[PDB]
Amino acid sequence: ILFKDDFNFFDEKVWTKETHEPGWTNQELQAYDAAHVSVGKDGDKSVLILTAERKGNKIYSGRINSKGKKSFKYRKIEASIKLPKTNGGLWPAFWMMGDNDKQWPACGEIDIMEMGEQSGMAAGDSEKQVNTAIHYGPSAAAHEQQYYKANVANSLQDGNYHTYSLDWDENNLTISIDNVKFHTFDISSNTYFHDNFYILFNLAVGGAFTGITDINKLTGLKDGQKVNMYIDWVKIL
Ligand SMILES: OC[C@H]1O[C@@H](O[C@H]2[C@H](O)[C@@H](O)[C@H](O[C@H]3[C@H](O)[C@@H](O)[C@H](O[C@@H]4[C@@H](O)[C@H](O)O[C@H](CO)[C@H]4O)O[C@@H]3CO)O[C@@H]2CO)[C@H](O)[C@@H](O)[C@@H]1O
Ligand SMILES: [Ca+2]
């Protein structure tokens, strides 16, 4: 183990909490703020907690990153995550961007796990449909992306913690879920995935990815509701 965070506390030398207005990216409905990121207990576990809540028409959630604090290259990274039921517009993600000052997508982006996609609800598989992706290219105008979408065998939104893994070498990005290989992206000739990347976790609410960009269509977080995304640990081997 090169690095482990067991989330016994919020380590400010490793993580930064993000603050953003609603609609900052992807037509998302939440504001991100520091108050919606915490570390606390989930029974016997100590966990990172991203909390999405809705107060009338205002939605708040949490997002963190390790940019300029912890980054790596060509290692396996694994995280143990418990997800809320996403149906109706929640959008959790565990992902990475290049730890450099290039403007997205030129920094490079690896989406290890995303759930909540519009097509997942449309196929009645919202608890099982996972998206993994890579985005890259020199500018927003020249944004390229490769995606893989499929259903895992069992619900990932079942009240238990599940393991999401990235194995990374100079040729391949391999995503696994509960030790079952999900997809491999070939990056052997892709210049964007050969430098250090930092880690992100977030719980977005609505957004283009979900198909839900109008708060009136947001059934997955009703007025007065709070929902939590939990990360027991993250480690890099
Ligand atoms: O500095 C100039 C300008 O920056 C503005 O914010 C930018 C930010 O710099 C940029 O990194 C951000 O990029 C986001 C993309 O717009 C968004 O599409 C992408 O979404 C990703 C998906 O690609 C991925 O599949 O899944 C993840 C997880 O679900 C998802 O979030 O995310 C990138 C990274 O956040 O765009 C911002 C808005 O343009 C500032 O707001 C502005 O003041 C500055 O002038
Ligand atoms: Ca823990």
Image (cartoon, rainbow, N blue to C red):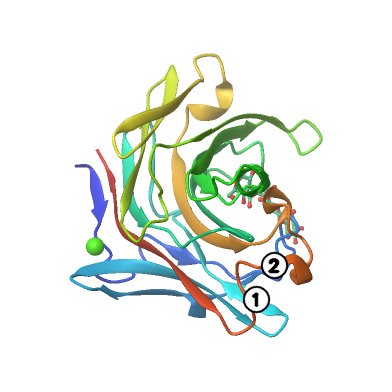
Q: Position of residue 103 (x, y in %)?
A: 68, 44
116 displayed left or right of 48: right
**Where in the image, quadrant-wise, is ligand 2 located?**
bottom left
The three-letter code of the residue at mark 1 reads Ile
Residue beneath label 2, please? 218
Is there any visible trace of residue 84 in the rendered image?
yes
Q: Is mark 1 within 8 Å of ligand 1?
A: no
The residue at 31%/40% (across/down) is 178
Residue beneath label 1, please? 59
**Marker disc for residue 230:** none
Q: Nearer the viewer, residue 169 or 26?
A: 26
19 in relation to 107, above or below: below
Q: Earlier in the sequence, mark 1 or mark 2?
A: 1
Is mark 1 in CB contact (under 8 Å) with mark 2? Answer: yes
Is there any visible trace of residue 11 in the rendered image?
no
79 displayed left or right of 170: left
- Crowding at label 2, few (<14), some or many (≥20) Cα neighbours within 10 Å? many
Q: Regarding mark 2 in the picture, which secondary structure is present there?
A: loop
The three-letter code of the residue at mark 2 reads Leu
The residue at 62%/34% (across/down) is 135
Q: Position of residue 162 (x, y in %)?
A: 32, 49
Q: Nearer the viewer, residue 202 or 92?
A: 92
79 displayed left or right of 105: left
179 in relation to 116, above or below: above
Q: Regarding mark 1 in the picture, which secondary structure is present there?
A: strand
- Crowding at label 1, few (<14), some or many (≥20) Cα neighbours within 10 Å? many
Q: How many marks?
A: 2
Determine which quarter of the picture holds residue 45: bottom left
Q: Residue furthest top?
A: 189
